[PDB]
């Protein structure tokens, strides 16, 4: 599958303009391209977590800001593939991931999310700041 132009534009606007705090991406209906499913300017990490589907897959880019010894920001890429998502969805999202991820320059951190503990604020804060 391919990456929709709109997906790269969204990413550039987040990267260069801080236009969004996060972007959710997903396959279009035809399974032919990765499109933008949702964007948000909400600074609360919970507003991102509450958008993660129980039984479906997605990709996300999150502009994660944190304290250093001022502040720093790192762009985090997520795959979200919960155990209860259909196995065919998990597989098509997995085979299609590189199409999106390879097209994105300036990602600092990659998260492979399969459950809440792997995408929690504390785990991700640990990933961006300490690893």
Image (tube, helix red, strand yellow):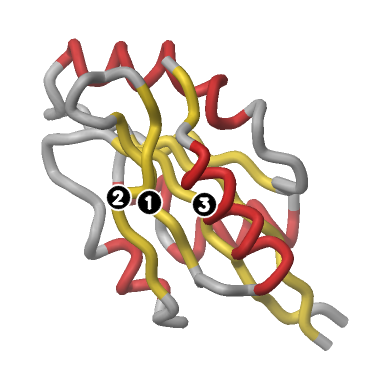
Q: Earlier in the sequence, mark 1 or mark 3?
A: 1
Q: Earlier in the sequence, mark 1 or mark 2?
A: 1
Q: Are marks 1 and 2 in contact (CB under 8 Å)?
A: yes
In this view, the residue in front, 119 or 105, is 105
Q: Say few, some or many: other residues with alpha carbon within 10 Å of mark 1 (under 14 / 14 to 19 / 20 or more).
A: many
> Residue 43, percent across and down?
46, 82
Location of mark 2 (residue): 37
Q: Quadrant of the N terminus?
A: top left
Left of 107 or right of it: where is 120?
left
Left of 39 or right of it: where is 98?
right
Q: CA distance from mark 2 to mark 3?
A: 12 Å
As drawn, 67 above or below 12? below
Q: Say few, some or many: other residues with alpha carbon within 10 Å of mark 2 (under 14 / 14 to 19 / 20 or more).
A: some
Q: Residue at x 37, y 48 (%)?
A: 36
Q: CA distance from mark 1 to mark 2?
A: 5 Å
Location of mark 3 (residue): 61
In this view, the residue in front, 57 or 15, is 15
Q: Residue at x 42, y 11 (%)?
A: 95
Q: Earlier in the sequence, mark 2 or mark 3?
A: 2
Q: Are marks 1 and 3 in contact (CB under 8 Å)?
A: no
Location of mark 1 (residue): 24
């Amino acid at each position: 599958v391919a990456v929709a132009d709109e997906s790269l534009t969204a990413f550039n606007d987040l990267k260069l303009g801080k236009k969004y705090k996060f972007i959710l991406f997903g396959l279009n209906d035809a399974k032919t391209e990765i499109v933008v499913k949702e964007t948000s300017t909400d600074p609360s990490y919970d507003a991102f977590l509450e958008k993660l589907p129980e039984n479906d897959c997605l990709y996300a880019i999150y502009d994660f800001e944190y304290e250093i010894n001022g502040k720093r920001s790192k762009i985090v890429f997520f795959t979200w593939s919960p155990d209860t998502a259909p196995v065919r969805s998990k597989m098509v999202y997995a085979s299609s991931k590189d199409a999106l991820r390879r097209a994105l320059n300036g990602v600092s951190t990659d998260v492979q999310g399969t459950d809440f503990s792997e995408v929690s604020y504390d785990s991700v804060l640990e990933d961006v700041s300490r690893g």
